[PDB]
Length: 43
Image (cartoon, rainbow, N blue to C red; front, side, top):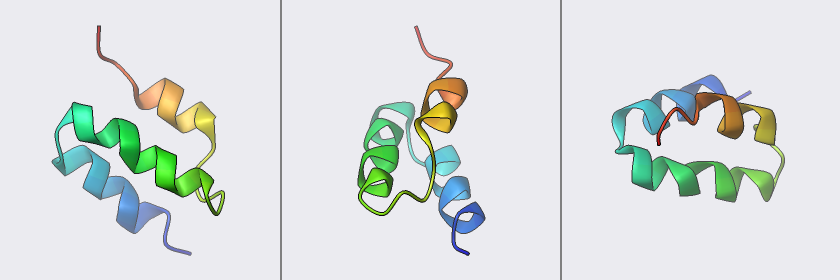
């Protein structure tokens, strides 16, 4: 499984780009929206 490897990426890249990091995932279903919503701590 390559869910943890990609996760670290979103942590490195800015928060703006991360928003898309989860978009491509949906394509296969790697990470659930629950993660994109939870991790999302911007306002």
